[PDB]
Image (cartoon, rainbow, N blue to C red; front, side):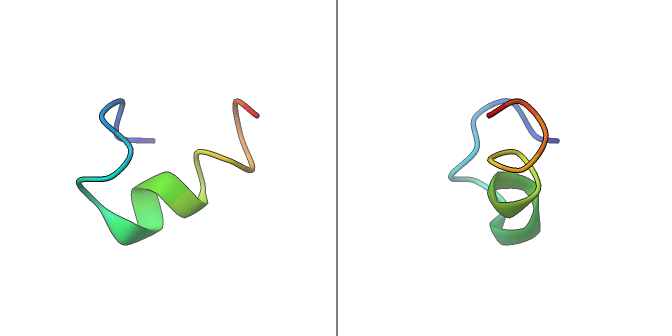
Length: 20
């Protein structure tokens, strides 16, 4: 998922579910 997080809605959403 996009590293900056808050640069892509789905990116941050599936970030917090993937690395978090």
